[PDB]
Length: 51
Length: 50
Image 1 (tube, rainbow over the protein chains, first blue to last red):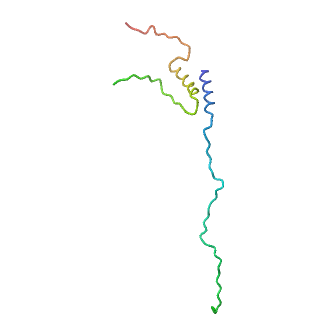
Image 2 (spheres, one colour):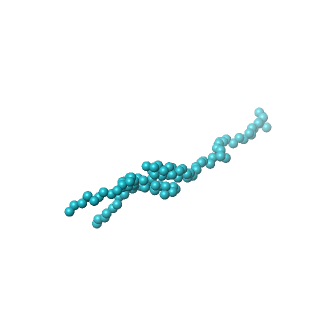
Image 3 (tube, rainbow over the protein chains, first blue to last red):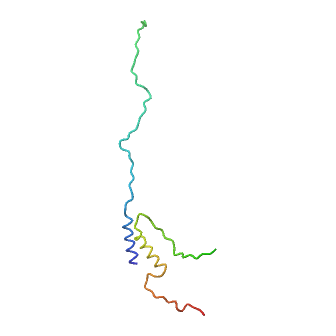
């Protein structure tokens, strides 16, 4: 019974080691909005006579 | 065809962990299976026939 406890305690230490890490690479990334209309600013002015 | 097999149980074993440590817990459980762990003396003289 003592040997079973001692070996289990040793096995607990051995199991407590790390394997790897995982994380997501997201910094420096933004979204892209979409603009449908070209912002032209031209306005045409014509006289009443049309000349 | 015929064959003889020694069962002796089946035990899971993992990787990344030292095998000697894992063998310790199975060794104790094996001794329980064979009735070896506690101090003993064999008494098999009377089991016979003529």
